[PDB]
Length: 270
Image 1 (tube, rainbow, N blue to C red):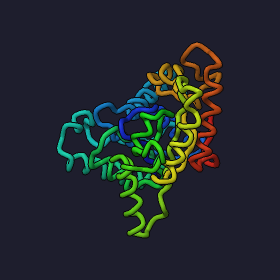
Image 2 (cartoon, rainbow, N blue to C red):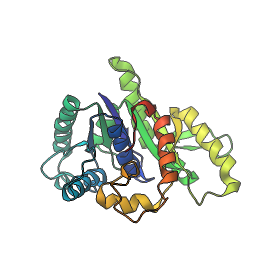
Image 3 (cartoon, rainbow, N blue to C red):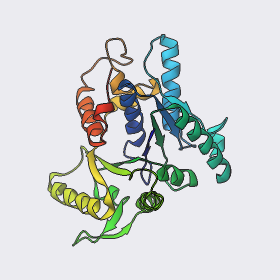
Image 4 (tube, rainbow, N blue to C red):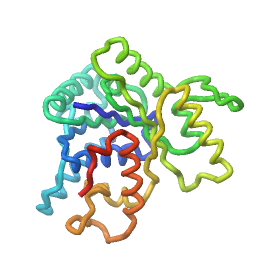
């Protein structure tokens, strides 16, 4: 089983839209995929897959679905419980997922918590969605404005470093991969392209991640969310919103994104 953990420091940058598209790409590639959502307050990924189950049940259409695992009988309430109860629920969900699935996708919220630390410690691949802007890069680390050398890694990056350190000191599993997925922004100014490219490459070198391409924000992802559908699901049998061509560029971005994660051999679409 391979464990993929999606996270970033503040929970933004389309993180849950990327997580649920990674899950459906691996389901259409024929894998069994578990999904564990550690954002106990907002549950964006868990709700997505509850919407998918409800929409498919109502339409009597069959599409692949992941094994969605909750950490307790009420994960919204679990958000306010002691961390030792949150860790217990996570360990039971992870044990089920490990017993049952080929990939385990764990979506994490912004911020630091015991369960987010534990998930990044167990990752084989950490995926960190990041918008292409100077303010966003500070969630990986601050750099000297002249030399672009790291002056302080973020708490997020320190957590990934600690997972890598422990994975080295144990030597029972393979090195963990870490990819930052850079989402292009429609507002990025051309005068900043060279400075943004240089800053993210300076961070990759000193923080130790590799860069892949992310997903541009598009209204279609928001329109599809309440149905639990991804761009990979759209077909002549599944078209829950007015037909448009608004999914073609998104489908190309998703192929490039999955290729950068090492997962092209395992990805499919409807």
